[PDB]
Structures are given as structure tokens and as C-alpha cells.
Amino acid sequence: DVVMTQTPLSLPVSLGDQASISCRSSQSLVHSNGNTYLNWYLQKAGQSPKLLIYKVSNRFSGVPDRFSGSGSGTDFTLKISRVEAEDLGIYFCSQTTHVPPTFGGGTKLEIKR
């Protein structure tokens, strides 16, 4: 199925700066109609998962607006107005456009060093 290459592998940023994680999709995530259904994700060391965008840029209910998604077809990104302690951890980007669902990736985001 469509592969999702998460990048970069590391994103050292201070809790306050803007962070933009990328994500590429083998043959784009455009369903048979011209619509893209992406699902950004984030998880800490054994904590409660958090979903940001659920299409391409719109933010899911609960997102502090600081999260923003964008991109074309075989490329996507998640810019954050400001990183917080909770934001730290590993990032991911899923997609419900193709089947079966992918769900995976892993961008390291543990503050700036």
C-alpha cells in the first residue's frame, strides 16, 4: 500500500519555537475522488495518544490550534506554533485514504539539545 516516510528523524526544538514535521506518501493520499484523509498523531513514553489534523490541515476537537497541517499529495507537514513539554515524544502520521490503513512512522521530538 501507500508507504509513509516520516521525517525528519529528529527535531530538536525549544519549548516555544515552531516545529514542522514532514511525511511523504508513496503515491499520494488522494482517494478516488480528489480528497485526502490524513491523520497526524503524537505519543509520549507510554501516555495518552493525541490526534492533531484528520485530513490535511483542519485540527481535531481538542487541538489547541497551535497545530497546523498542510502539504500536497505525496508530501505533508505539521507545523506547531510552539512546542510544549507534552509535545515532546515521538510523532507519527496516519492515513485512511487507502486500505488497509498504514499508521506508523516515528519522528523524534525531545526538545532542543
Image (cartoon, grey):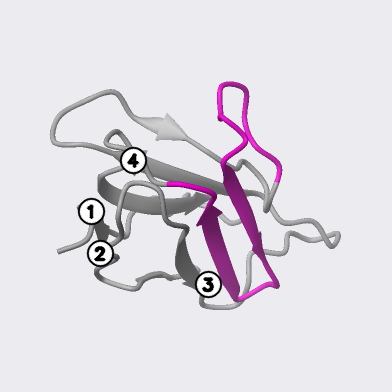
Residue underneath mark 4 = 87
Neighbour class for label 4 at 10 Å: few (<14), some, many (≥20)?
Answer: some
Q: Earlier in the sequence, mark 2 or mark 3?
A: 2
Image-based side of 54 in relation to 12, left or right = right
Q: Earlier in the sequence, mark 4 or mark 2?
A: 2
Q: Earlier in the sequence, mark 3 or mark 4?
A: 3
Give me the residue at 35% from left, 39% from top. 84
> Which marked residue is nearer to the observer: mark 2 or mark 3?
2
- What percent of the width, then of the height, locates residue 92? 37, 52
Image-based side of 95 in relation to 93, left or right = right
Callout 1 amino acid: Ile
Q: CA distance from mark 2 to mark 1?
A: 5 Å
Residue 71, which numbered label?
none
Residue 25, which numbered label?
3
Residue 60 visible (yes or no): yes
Residue underneath mark 2 = 12
> Which marked residue is nearer to the observer: mark 4 or mark 1?
1
Dot 4 falls on a residue whose secondary structure is: loop
Dot 1 falls on a residue whose secondary structure is: loop
Give me the residue at 13% from left, 36% from top. 45
Callout 4 amino acid: Asp
Q: CA distance from mark 3 to mark 4?
A: 24 Å
Neighbour class for label 2 at 10 Å: few (<14), some, many (≥20)?
Answer: few
Q: Which residues are magenta?
A: 58-82
Q: Quadrant of residue 17?
A: bottom left
Residue 111, which numbered label?
1
